[PDB]
Image (cartoon, rainbow over all chains, first blue to last red; front, side, top):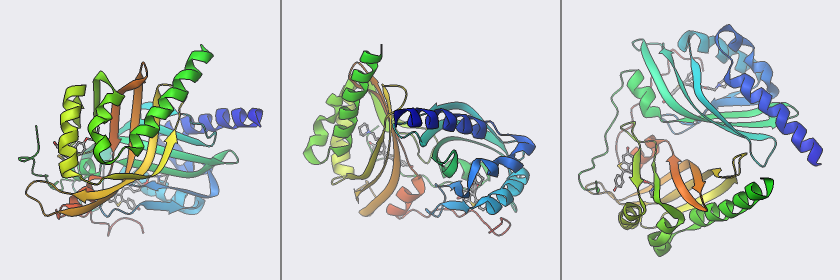
Length: 154
Length: 154
Ligand SMILES: O=C(c1ccc(OCCN2CCCCC2)cc1)c1c(-c2ccc(O)cc2)sc2cc(O)ccc12
Ligand SMILES: O=C(c1ccc(OCCN2CCCCC2)cc1)c1c(-c2ccc(O)cc2)sc2cc(O)ccc12
């Protein structure tokens, strides 16, 4: 059992590293790192509900959209965390690039991210990214509300 | 080396468990889980800058404010992740409780959280919590902006 777990963790880490380093046109093939029913998405949005992209066909379509709306995106400062579950990794990183959203001015978007990767049979079954949406609001020119801090100790 | 790493990870895990289960008046003593120069705080805020509380004395003072502002806070759905670093843990969980911020109506706040715990010599050197601030805005009656999604594939 231990040999199987160690083997799974070392392979899975290679997939996480490949995912994090996928840039440019190679993003069009990143759905091949997922299971056929694999899910990937953004868990932190304005609405409070995740934007989850389900299955390889939809994952490949999102990649096409992502090459237009995040054309030069890169992950930086990547720190990969293995866990006690050989099939579950976390990654802390930053991301940055142009943001080209329909109906908004072209901007520059930078944020801090956490990613969760869960594996099944050597491929990603579930990828989730978590960030602070206020920074994406700022990149799009959307006003961010401010919590009033006068009564809070500082 | 392996003996020392295994011992560190087992002890540190117990501290993470104790931290996550601390509620009520026991919150007043939770700063004793930190190093004298330990830091804890919220890394995801409206301003984009962390709210970091530095040093055991200030951590103890924030606990007094925390018991006023979040009088019945509970962490739920706790999943603790050990990592390859025996001194670094991540936690995925939910949190809920009344929110009683100065000058806002009393609310009920629920959110999903990620926590990072870094240890030094048996105590927490750095705790950081990450969430979606839009859910805290909702709990305070603050309007959340909406990204227009008409041009995005759905
Ligand atoms: O910026 C995004 C977004 C960014 C990345 C996403 O997923 C990243 C993970 N990735 C998805 C498939 C490929 C591999 C994993 C999802 C939404 C937002 C949106 C989006 C983008 C494209 C699309 O077709 C539908 C909705 S909508 C939105 C609202 C917000 O408040 C914040 C971000 C957003
Ligand atoms: O909700 C918080 C907040 C909550 C928890 C925080 O820290 C958590 C860690 N802390 C130290 C270690 C032990 C546990 C408490 C910090 C800010 C926000 C604020 C706060 C609360 C109390 C205070 O005295 C000063 C500022 S201000 C603010 C603005 C936002 O956009 C979001 C949250 C907030």
